[PDB]
Amino acid sequence: GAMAPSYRVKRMDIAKNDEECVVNAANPRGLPGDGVCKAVYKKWPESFKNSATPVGTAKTVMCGTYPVIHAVGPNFSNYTESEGDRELAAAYREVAKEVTRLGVNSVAIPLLSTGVYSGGKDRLTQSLNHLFTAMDSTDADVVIYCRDKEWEKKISEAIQMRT
Ligand SMILES: COc1ccc([C@@H](Cc2nnn[nH]2)NC(=O)c2ncnc3[nH]ccc23)cc1
Ligand SMILES: [Cl-]
Image (tube, rainbow, N blue to C red; front, side, top):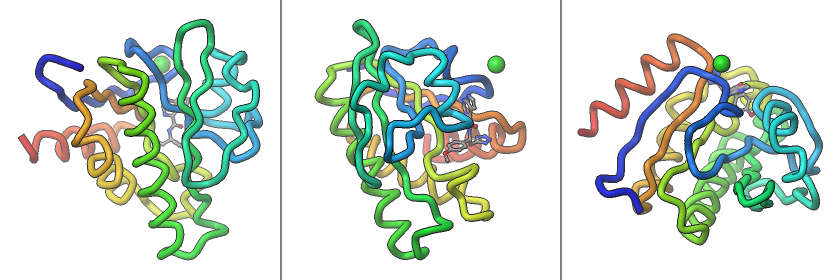
């Protein structure tokens, strides 16, 4: 694990991360998709071999020796708020189990169920809180990747508030 486990946020493409493994915001069918998923597909295409997995789960596939954790968050256009909240929290708990199993000292993670899976709602706080609930008991350094300037500021403030 990391010597002093921390949370950090960076506004840049997760495909250029400087961590020991990456979490993909995957679709259940293991398709190239769009957004984070498409950037992960272009960078680590080999990691999409048998990567299909249900909503609320995570499946790791190696690209060489680099682990890609395919985490499937719910699409809030299909799920109710209550059921979608439960599956989002579960996808993050499965990410924590995988990061621990892998023995990595760091992980790059995006905010699950935001963007096209958000059902047109702002889910920054909801997704980030479920991320913290799952990752707080792990000792990996966590680096959150985002693309929006206002989101970078809000994530940074949320990290600092707890320290
Ligand atoms: C439906 O799943 C999604 C998950 C995350 C996302 C969004 C959430 C977001 N939007 N503003 N800051 N954050 N993030 C990215 O699109 C993103 N983040 C990191 N690296 C990237 N490389 C290429 C894209 C990309 C959308 C959709
Ligand atoms: Cl970039």
